[PDB]
Image (cartoon, rainbow, N blue to C red; front, top):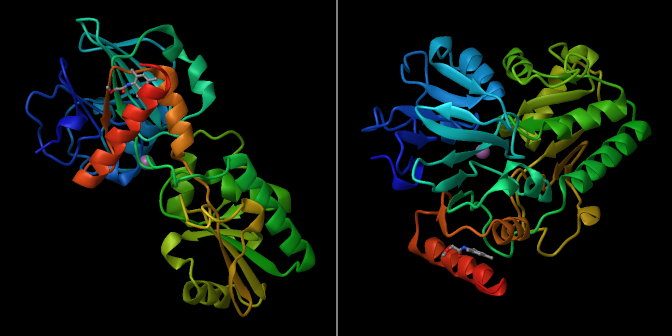
Length: 341
Ligand SMILES: COCC(=O)Nc1c(C)cc(C)cc1C
Ligand code: NI
């Protein structure tokens, strides 16, 4: 049963709905971004049209082996016609290749589906500024006022400065960064850039990053772990046992590990500033949890919605409980009434 919030009324379209088999009456499947909760179900045996960004299409072809003839990449910021309906893809400020989708229905209704996004004032000067939006399908991941986090820029500043200090003090320290999907590439790339190193990683992860068209990426990534003092490992291995084991494997080249876990939100943020963040330490291993988010804070989300002024909001995250649903609807009404509507 495909939920109603993945269906676009008045069209043959669904969004991020690949885990339900053949959806009744769906003539085109849209994919907002290459994260597994959204792509779950796609493979080389999928034979319906898939619409997506160029970067997402590269990942579909190379990582999942979807046949080229079924992949329909669209340029960003360009009016395109799909099965007789005008659509536009907009940058979602999430992970690489992530998009929001504007649909212009034949009857004059305009719908924005945000996919996963981190709202930014820069969005207020895209093609969104050019017409009224009637229905908003909203990424409500952090739709509660306790969810505050710093800007991405402040978090990268903290990580750069921490890593540069540690390695300048001890030239035999290794830096490790955790990953389990695309996104948050700036964490490991900015650290490698300040240390004059490439980022070393598995063949599989190097393959994934090569699909992204990031400029000068051959210049910052490698599969040669020996030449690199910044290593990427699976997020599962960013703990004291996993990191002790990795250090053993580096053959006496290194005597200390500084590791980063770039999680979305921690509850340090409620009582603490970014400058006040401290690691967990055991022996010669330190682990920093840094609040690098690729989803809107509560205040960022509020500003975006109050600017857009949609007639109806359909949440796409935290929809499974009555308590969550009720809480989100109360915030939406607050936001409306504060602007005088
Ligand atoms: C009825 O639900 C939708 C809604 O409340 N929308 C809305 C919000 C959230 C804020 C502003 C400033 C204006 C509008 C129209
Ligand atoms: Ni996502």
